[PDB]
Image 1 (cartoon, rainbow, N blue to C red):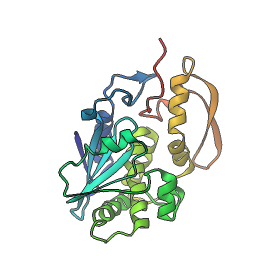
Image 2 (spheres, rainbow, N blue to C red):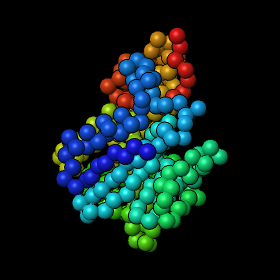
Image 3 (cartoon, rainbow, N blue to C red):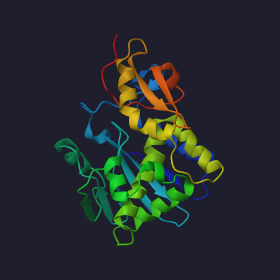
Length: 258
């Protein structure tokens, strides 16, 4: 499986930008593009030898962890840290079988009893996304927390908070140029802030947007989708045009019309 590398150690807007770019390149094949927006590979009929990509994360503290993402949705399904690998609770027989193809030589394999969805993680973390800071520092720390989990160094709430940091700074950033942009800003000015309403709203609407777009009539949505700006004010989306600068990847929802 392909491996993309990134380190928080001396991270710059450029290093992070090159990183996210390489991830998108490994997530999509460039076969499916609609209205100038790349669509992730359809899960139906996808060979297992092309199912995942690995994201190796390192930090100034010289520690490393490797995240395993599913190319069909960019979701983080588990990670490896030294002699141990942990997987979120599979959601169906297919996914449970699939993950057995990852980190095949790790001494110890574990499968969490909870899922990797935000609702669950926030609950375990004891904080919502709107109250969990993002930036190079939080990522630096997250990497450390994931690494010391198997040795009893990381408490569950802190591990959950860590996943939430990694998922938004890697997967969400890959999905949205907008979100990638906010992270770049954080890195440039070395600031540590929780995600604003525009970020949360986008994170929550990825699937809907992907469908609205793909099911659109020449790019015109049947029904508008409500998003939020940074000051939390409402603003409707009726067309894919205004999303081109915003969404970088879509989950496959349907076949494109002729």
